[PDB]
Image (tube, rainbow over the protein chains, first blue to last red):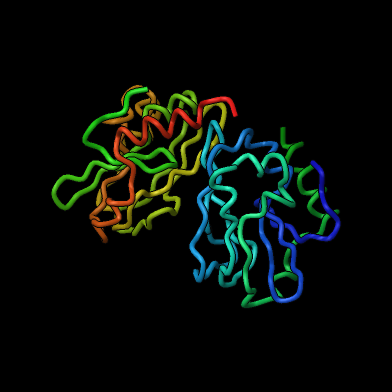
Length: 131
Length: 131
C-alpha cells in the first residue's frame, strides 16, 4: 500500500517511471504485498519489443506464478539482471531496486491511459473491498 | 514432492513429456503442493498456439490463483476436459491424469533450455529455503 506520486499505474499493478526517452517498469508495493515472498523472476531479452497489455515476464512467489503485462509498448534496452540472484528486491524495494526493465517507448501517448497515484489508490481500495 | 525422471521442467513449475511429435504439459507435484486444493482450472481451446514463457491458462485454488505458462511453443491439439469436472486431479495426479494440454511442438530445441529432473529438484530447494 505505499503509492508514489510521480509514476503511472496499470490496473494489473505495474508502475511506469518515464524520464525523458526511457521508461522504467516494475510492480507496485500492493502487488508484492499480495503475492507474498518473491522467489524467482523471469525477464525478456534486450532488443525485444513489448506491447501494452501483453505479458513480458513473470514473478513467482512461494505459492504462485504471476505474469506481468507491459503497461506501454516499446523496445527493451536494459533488464535488471540483479533480480535473478536477488528476487526479494521486489518485496523490499518495488519502486527502486526492484525495477524490472527499461524501455524506449514507441507510442508514448499510451501513458495518457494510465492511472495516476490517487486513481490507483482508489482502484486498490475497490479491489480489496470486493472482500 | 515427487519429481519424475524422464520429464523436462520450467522454473514456473510446469513439466513437459515429449512423445513423438506430441508434448503433454501439466503442473508439478511441488506446484500443486504449494497451491493447495485446486477448485477451478482455465484451459485454452484446440487450434490455438501457445508460446514459450506465455500464459495459456490458470489454476485457481482455495488460496491463490496462478498463471500457467507454456514451457515450449506449439499448437494446442487436445485439452483435458476431465479437469473441468474434476479440478482435484491436479492435486492427486499432477503427472498423469492431471495433465492439462497436449501440443504439437513448433521448435523442439526449446526443450534444451528446460531444467532436467536433478536441476529442478535443486531449484525447488533454493526456493523453499529461508532467505
